[PDB]
Amino acid sequence: AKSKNHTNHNQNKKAHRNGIKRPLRKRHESTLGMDVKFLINQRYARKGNLSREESVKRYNERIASQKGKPKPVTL
Amino acid sequence: GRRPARCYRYCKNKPYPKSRFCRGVPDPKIRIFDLGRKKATVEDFPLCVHLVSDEYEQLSSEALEAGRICCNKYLVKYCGKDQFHIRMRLHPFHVIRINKMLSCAGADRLQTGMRGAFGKPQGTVARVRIGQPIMSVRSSDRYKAQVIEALRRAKFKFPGRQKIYVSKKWGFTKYERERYEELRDDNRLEPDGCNVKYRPEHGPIAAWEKAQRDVYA
Amino acid sequence: TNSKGYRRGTRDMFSRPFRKHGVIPLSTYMRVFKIGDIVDIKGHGAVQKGLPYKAYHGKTGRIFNVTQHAVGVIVNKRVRGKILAKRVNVRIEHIHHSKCREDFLRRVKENERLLKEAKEKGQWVSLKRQPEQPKKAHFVKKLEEPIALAPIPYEFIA
Amino acid sequence: KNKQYFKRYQVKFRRRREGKTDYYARKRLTFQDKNKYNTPKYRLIVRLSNKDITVQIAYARIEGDRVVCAAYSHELPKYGIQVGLTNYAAAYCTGLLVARRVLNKLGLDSLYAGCTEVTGEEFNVEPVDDGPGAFRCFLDVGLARTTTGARVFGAMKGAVDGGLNIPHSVKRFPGYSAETKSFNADVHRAHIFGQHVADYMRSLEEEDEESFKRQFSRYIKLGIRADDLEDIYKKAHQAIRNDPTHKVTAKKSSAVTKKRWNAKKLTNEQRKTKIAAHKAAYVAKLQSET
Amino acid sequence: MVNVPKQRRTFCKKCKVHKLHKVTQYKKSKERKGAQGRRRYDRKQQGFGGQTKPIFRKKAKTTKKIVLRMECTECKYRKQTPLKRCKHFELGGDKKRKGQMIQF
Amino acid sequence: VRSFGIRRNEKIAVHCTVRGAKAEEILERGLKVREYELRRENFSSTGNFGFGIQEHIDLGIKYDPSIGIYGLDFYVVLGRPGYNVNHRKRKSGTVGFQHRLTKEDAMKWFQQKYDGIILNT
RNA sequence: AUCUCUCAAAUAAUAACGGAGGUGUCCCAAGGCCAGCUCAGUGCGGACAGAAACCACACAUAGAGCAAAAGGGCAAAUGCUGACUUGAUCUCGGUGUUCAGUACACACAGGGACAGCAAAAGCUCGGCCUAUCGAUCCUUUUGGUUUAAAGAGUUUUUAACAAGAGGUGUCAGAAAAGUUACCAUAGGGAUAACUGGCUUGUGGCGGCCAAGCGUUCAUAGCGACGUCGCUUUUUGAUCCUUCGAUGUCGGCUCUUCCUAUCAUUGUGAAGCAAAAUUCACCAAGCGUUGGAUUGUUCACCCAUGCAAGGGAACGUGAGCUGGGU
RNA sequence: GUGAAGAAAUUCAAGUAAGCGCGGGUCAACGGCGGGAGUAACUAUGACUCUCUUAAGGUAGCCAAAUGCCUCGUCAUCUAA
RNA sequence: GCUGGUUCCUUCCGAAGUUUCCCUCAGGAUAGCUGGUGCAUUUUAAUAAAUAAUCUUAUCUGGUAAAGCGAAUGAUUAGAGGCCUUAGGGUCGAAACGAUCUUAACCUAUUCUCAAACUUUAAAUGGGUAAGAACCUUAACUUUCUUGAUAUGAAGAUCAAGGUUAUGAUAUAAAUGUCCCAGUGGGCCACUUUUGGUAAGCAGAACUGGCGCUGUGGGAUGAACCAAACGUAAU
RNA sequence: GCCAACGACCAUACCACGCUGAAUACAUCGGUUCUCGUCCGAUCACCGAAAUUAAGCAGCGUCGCGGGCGGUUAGUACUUAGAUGGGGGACCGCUUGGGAACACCGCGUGUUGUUGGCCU
């Protein structure tokens, strides 16, 4: 027989009882399914981060090897 | 087969349209909507009187057949045979479905228990709102008594409740009667079948010019 | 007795507008899209290469993976009722730029600057928004045509 | 007829109404991959006219194309090309011209000398190492049929012999017969040196004087005999590599609102006074008879 | 009718390039025992049981899909790739000829 | 169409076009057999004019009974200098009220040269 | 099992044996790609030339076409024709849908490899997008230059692993004909036949307005097309109550009640001379029969009669009967 | 049982009984036993004629049958009905 | 997989009749709802410069109500105007080819009425996201790379500067595991919306609230109506 | 005031018609030997200039079409929310708030980017 197949009464009273449950706000998120390198490049820049204080100044002195960079403003 | 309309008096559904494959439907003879001197111009019939409704009534089309043949057969008796223009302002463009018991011959043996529930088409109906005129009689101002009394005998064939406007219109125009004349008197309105023309100005020149030609020369 | 399947009831989600048919204007391919940017989804009905499904048109979310010519957006889809975080790839013409941050990012400038001009005068900041207060007490002169001006009905006779 | 036609009709774009672009190359050229976000395309426009060809390097942007550099064949009378500006060989030196008019902007003049001895071989440039990789460009011909040996590919042949890295094949260079290929490089050395224009004259030196009153007239006005055309076109190649001065101009100016000039557009007042007299003139045409 | 041109240049997995490949049809290879599944269905059946296993009735499909062994022409490697369900299919073909009046 | 049994891709008809240095000699050949006072229409409103002929041998050819006779229709399209603007790939465009050819431009030019009257029936 | 438009109430979701349809295929091009050209139709022209074709010039915002249903979509295409083609391939995961947020299946965004077209940019992982499909077990084939058969060697064989195939359409997938009035059990008022309830297509039904008929005369008496209400014993419609049982047709007998008046009492009207009759009002007080046939109820027939109403507890089986089923 | 190929298991081939298949006989064996058209000096009816099918088209006979739906068939009788 | 029963008292919390699959439709599994038991801890945890859920702001989306047919498609009434040469009767005329009107269309400007499977326009009620230190800039560093002559872009690792922390009102505590533990997977009623039916105390859906589980006050009477939710008592 | 190339948004740009257009230009335009395509040098392809501003095109004109915008139809239609509000029913009214649409009237007729260039 036929009384009540497929209703929605009590369905958002239930879904609002142990309530509606926003997901999350995660600082870091999974990189699962990203562009696969991209991520091998960032896995190569993550290793080579070596200078905190030392070489990070030094290459400006190497900029002055061409007395700076007058020319490469174009490309 | 000719189903009564005690069972079909309301706007019970969002209205059935008329498809383009269901031929086998009954052909009515509600083909007539204007009656009287339909060819006379606006200058011949300046009085206009409507039969305005008072509910969101759904009218049958049986009632609208009677409402025109009633008002014809006083106005061909008490108005002169051409001195009017009965016009139905209201067309019966809907379908009613009648699942009747045509369950004789007694041995099909499955006919319907509740299998299946297709509807069966046996006519039309015409839906009405409040303040929606059903007929309008365009005539001359002399028969004003003869027309407002003609429409009383059109009330008693319609269900519901009707109210009888005499218009400030000049016949079947959109214009007020005095406001008709002021716009008419120089060039600005033009005759037609039963209606007028509305500010022929823009554009560009010759329509202003040639309509100024013939009113001058 | 159904919907099912995948593009049903899209006679108006992916209908084109009135007379905006035709070649997609070529700025759509020229926009720059970054990772963590926020983005809307209006499934463009003239591009069949990876439309969003109909449950994501209308919905905004954050990009987090950009590719050659599509973008992987994170859209919140409510199920019953536990709101999920989906991970949708769509192309570019099924995406627009949000504006919902754009006002705020000009509010971050000015609250940096309304404190910057008040960096020198010192006092006082008054940074945060207010909703609409009551107006004040005025007084208004006629001054200009004293009263009445007096509307009084007569509304039926018709 | 055709009145509710206009309510529903909408227009193809602007430059499909003028017939200028095609928007089916325009999407597909200027498409960069949306993960190499904003590094531009730098394609190569070659557009040709009855008088004067045109080559511009450009990359599109949201707000119209940016243009890095442009070089026309009208600059060539500086470098010795007086007449015959839409040869294939006159199209060669223009694409040679921007390929040196642009590397001065980048300072890529020490590197990528290019095919200094032009003979007609596909010398795509080599990336000189430990530093600046070669400039990249892609060909945009647009609305000309890329038939085997059209004029637009010498402009390409100007660029790849200038030094710009463009991927190309040879199948639309002249004389590479597709029945069957026939890498015949030397027909360039007859075409890029313009000699078959000259050998058209050398096969018409003898028949008609009126042939010189016909086509290749005005070589006769400058005494340009049919023998030294290579010597023009050889001399241009070493002279285009002298100085692309980028066409500096210091008129500054005679430009502003001279003289009016183009029939300003009649505001509504003097529109109304035009209609006021016209309605007054028509009753005056009517009051004449009465 | 589904023609297949009986040659094609697809991916020879052994040569690791595209090689010219001759095409065929897979047909069937009957059930030759002793496969262990027959060696079992020849003992569950044996004396006094009354038919132990399902006898599949209720055939519903009208077609089957077709598998083409595609032999390499250099290294004679083969490859089974299916197609869609097709009710008529002849390879070899007499390739379609277009814009053509039926004659005589 | 099956009223005359012609079929899709049956190749019922032959046609050929002539541009320049051969039109103006073939037409005057076609005009002597036309005895060129040709009737008035014969004149499409877009300035074009064509005509039927019979008995195709009199166009300067031998009778050649191996091939027999063949009835012909001619059609001549006139123009002005400039109509390639209508028919180019790059920067195309239409023409205007004039240079579009009226029928009078096609009747005058037939009255002026070739001296034929238009037989205004 | 599945798809499209609607229902669907402006996210998405939503149901009925609701409405209109579709699918179990078709395509070596109808797949790919590069180039070229633009369609429905209308208009004016041209021997045989109408609807006849075919050539030909202008107009022509898609009114054409796109294998097929429907919907979107497409104009230098995704349409038409031509070039050349095999990306309708191989591999690894991930996402969208269905969602339990599982699997197939379809689709999508990519990495790797090999390629096709293209001058190149680029485009292609089948069909312009939304349907066109199938586990385990078993059989099978293709693949390693394979692993195992456990005392050891080689060869046959068998098996294993990987990717396909053979199919379950009741489509998340048993291998399956009837009958029982000779019957049975577990239950069911989740479910019929039966009373009661609600309902009215049917039944039955009385006012409004008059086209009329009524010789003349609208309304003495009727009253077309309309229109509005009233009753529920039938006919159904439903499935509320009862299946650990409400005796299920009638007739016989015997009560009372109702008017929707057949006759009688009291009156009004008439196309009311008398007689006879018809219309209407107050009226349920007293009546409303004997028989032939049939199990029936209405039924018709003979006869009585100045003059032979209609109905209510489907009245009434520990009242009878047992003719019907 | 027989031959052949193989190192063998095994695989192949000839041959292949009764049934079945083909064929004959049987219905006091199970059963079955037709249509449409046109026609006779009034209408009616159709002795006849065409014709389509089938294994054979229900013959002698009986019948609104305890067997006929329509049906309370139509006619006569029995009856006051 | 069905019927009947299933034995103390108080205290606390407190449902479901829905989804998907099943030779499944009086049953299961499965998620939702429930209780238990913890645990982690916050200048929204114990002597906030940070979360979270109705309004505001800002910004996206939508094609229903209304509107429309003098916009497409689809029906569609009425006449008007027209060179016409499509013209039907004719007519003055041998026909008229001279002409006359007429009538049919056709064309032009109108007009009456509409449409679950029609749209130009387009609400309210709604759906999404945002609203600051997990921020804002500044720097030069990083990368094998695919792209790039700053070996620039991007995504990052460490420094420099940052006022008063960036709508409102709320916090009966919130966050999270396990036992996916019990029961349930027959629902009925109602506003407004709505489909089938002629109607129905009928059938089927959308929303909210109830009844089921719920007494008390009111409607004489009653599962749902209107008030109001309930420890024992006084006022 | 301009022109070309390349565009962006894609009718305020479109359509019809008419007028004008210095220069830079663009074209129109001359040819077929080569490259090259065609039944046909028309289309493309390649050669280079005699002719012309007719036309394209550019600028404008029109109580133009359309399309754009604004007022206004209108606090209207509809709609959240409330009542033990009306009515026999259809349906209506009130309260609390959000609030359109055709038409109609007006007003506008593309704005601009990068690069070379003309300057009446």
Image: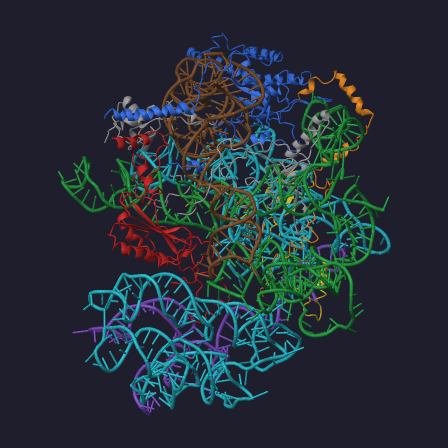
Chain colours: A orange, B red, D blue, E yellow, G cyan, H purple, I green, J brown
Q: In which quarter of the image is residue B10?
A: bottom left
Given residues I145 and H6, the one toward you in this image is I145
Given residues D216 and E5, the one toward you in this image is D216
Relative to G101, is G77 above or below?
above
Relative to H13, is G48 above or below?
above
Given residues F48 and D204, the one toward you in this image is F48
Q: In this view, does I122 lie to the left or right of A35?
A: left
Percent x, y for residue A11? 64, 55
Q: Residue at x 68, y 29 (%)?
A: C114
Relative to D228, is G283 above or below?
below
Percent x, y for residue G152? 85, 52
Q: Is residue B106 left or right of residue E1?
A: left
Res. C12 in view:
no
Relative to A36, is H51 above or below?
below
Given residues B75 and B58, the one toward you in this image is B75
Can you say which quadrant of the picture contains the N terminus of chain D? Answer: top left
Can you say which quadrant of the picture contains the C terminus of chain D? Answer: top left
